[PDB]
Length: 62
Length: 72
Length: 148
Ligand SMILES: [Zn+2]
Ligand SMILES: [Zn+2]
Image (cartoon, rainbow over all chains, first blue to last red):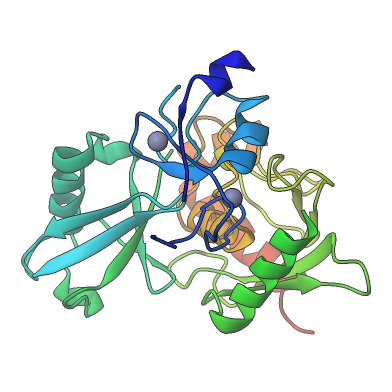
């Protein structure tokens, strides 16, 4: 879980759409960017990486 | 012309192509840009699987068209 | 979870995925039924194949149980309708949707994979006697996906 904490987490600008929940980013959301340049919701990528270790898009390991 | 190739996950790549390019040539350029061997690629456009040896003009693929890539 | 499923349903309503349709059965949003048109190149051309889609409560973090309810003569599909597909097991990703899974299934119908088969008998027939495979597959399609 601390591996999840040691990740590029930043504040919210751009809207786009998180590929997991398919939802537009809004204020209050905190984004998390992976080394593979892919950015997601903190909530979504945290619930994903809790049981897997791959990026949801390009499947590069983290 | 330039085309888009989107994976199922959402990986969007932009390809420089000729309408006379075969599907195998497009797979070779996909390997050049992303590094996946062509034998593992399956290209689809307009819900139709693209055959190796067919050209882009066979399928009426035009500017800013979007193919879908399936891995294996 | 639920809102993800509703978003996928609305996106299917806006963008019909060509030779594929899908949607809930009754008032249960977690049990979907889908129809896939046989690829025009394939021996499954002209047929309509039904599928059941069971979503887990932790979707999209777990892949759904997608099974063929229409009988089909395919090396990667057994009599229980189970599909030996990469993204329905080890290669699942929460960025995938039902539309993309149906695209994958249509691609599998067009281009089978006999080297990693689910029904080894059909794989042997496919890689050794292609005439018999195509014949039995076409008559299976006409007997279980046409007429009515
Ligand atoms: Zn999200
Ligand atoms: Zn990635």
